[PDB]
Image 1: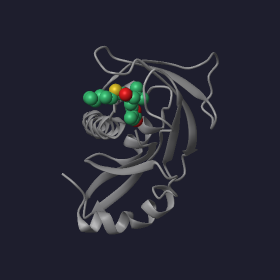
Image 2 (image 1 turned 120 degrees about the vertical axis):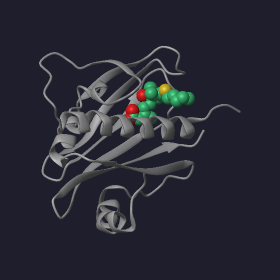
Image 3 (image 1 turned 90 degrees about the vertical axis):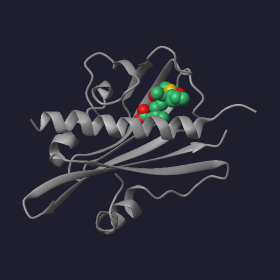
Image 4 (image 1 turned 180 degrees about the vertical axis):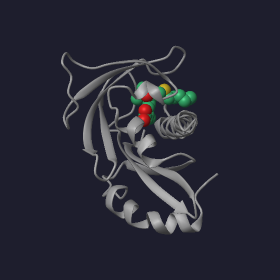
Length: 175
Ligand SMILES: CCCCCCSC1=C(C)[C@](O)(/C=C/C(C)=C\C(=O)O)C(C)(C)CC1=O
């Protein structure tokens, strides 16, 4: 369940525009994709909701935002992760929200974990071939490379699961 040459071709321009980074030495990047057999805007409605990432993020326990919270670039959230993980909390600034083009992204700017300078971008993309509408989501990130330990593996495993749960959650709401 990875993207076909055609989906790849269609998404080539989105990758160039939102998922291409100028790396700092000592940093790395990753790109993940997820087909979702559901409508784009449904997917998009969950992805944009920067105050409720628990809706589709596997390992989030709770997420609080400030009083009278309004969703704008520069606003933060404090995420608490579930028990038994090697992280407790994360605090995150929304770096992008384009409802027109369906692009968000955020940076992890503190918390009790070991990701250093993590920033990701998430984009939702509509597909159609004779009466079948479906969605592909792309998510990329940049982080610092890490004696101990193993932040890339953590990041890849977490985004992959979140993308699988996103799909599961949105395909249900397509009820
Ligand atoms: C080793 C089994 C995979 C679990 C390790 C991931 S625990 C974890 C989790 C679940 C995180 O939310 C990571 C989230 C990430 C990388 C992406 C995202 O949430 O979109 C942080 C608290 C920010 C960093 C972190 O360490």
